[PDB]
Image (spheres, rainbow, N blue to C red):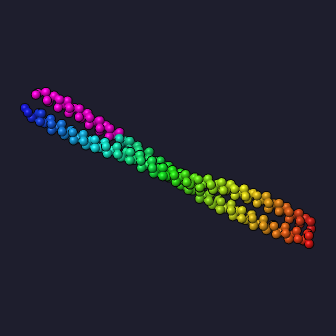
Amino acid sequence: GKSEISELRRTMQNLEIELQSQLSMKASLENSLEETKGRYAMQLAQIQEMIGSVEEQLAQLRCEMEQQNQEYKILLDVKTRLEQEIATYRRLL
Amino acid sequence: TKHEISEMNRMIQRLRAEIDNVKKQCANLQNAIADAEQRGELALKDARNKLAELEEALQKAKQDMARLLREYQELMNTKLALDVEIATYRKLLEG
């Protein structure tokens, strides 16, 4: 007669431990998610930074490459005038 | 007195339903993390890729410059070489 209420505490308290086990799982999952979201956000931020550095270096070089072909052109517009100049002196002979 | 078995059971019903929800919750969670790392590994992948792509363009560019510099030097060698022809020919003129 009195056994039923007894089996119920047994099964009741058993559930309470399964709850504890579920909450522990849930809590441990929450940890892992936030932690995941962190590791990648920061590794990515790290790579994004390396990327920007290279892009600047590249941009600079092209600006310098701009000035260096420009410099060549000048040099040429001169070497040509000179060719013209010797051409003329040779024409005098 | 008899009323005790009636609620212990109502409660056991409630507790299971509670546990069923933590279970249903922990499942969406794993998916979320799964989705977290799926999304993630890809961004790093993509990132890494862009990086080398540029590392590549840089070195590529580096050489092109080195080249144009040889190109300029070589153009200069001749220009200063014409400078001395102009000289030896100005001389011949004005004795």
Quarter in which the C terminus of chain A is drawn: bottom right
- Residue, x 91% and y 70% (percent of image)? B94
Residue B56 place in picture, x, y as percent: 57, 56
The residue lying furthest to the bottom in this view is: B95
Rendered residue at 68%/60% (across/down): B68
Percent of width and height locating residue A82: 83, 62
Quarter placement of the N terminus of chain A: top left
**Vertical side of A5 occupied by B64: above or below:** below
Residue B40 image offset from top left, x and y in percent = 44, 47
Numbered label tally:
0
Image-based side of B40 in relation to B67, left or right: left
Q: Which residues are magenta?
A: B1-28
Q: Main secondary structure of the magenta part?
A: helix
The question of residue B26 being in magenta is answered with yes
Q: Residue at x 79, y 60 (%)?
A: A78
Query: Does the rendering let one see residue B86?
Result: yes
The structure residue drawn at horizontal position 21% and vertical position 38%, both measured from the top left corner, is: A15
Q: Is residue A77 left or right of residue B26?
A: right
Q: Is residue B53 visible?
A: no
* Relative horizontal placement of residue A47, taking residue B23 as reference (left or right): right
Q: Position of residue A70 (x, y in %)?
A: 72, 56
Is residue A1 one of those drawn in magenta?
Answer: no
Q: Quadrant of residue A88?
A: bottom right
Is A64 in front, or is B54? A64
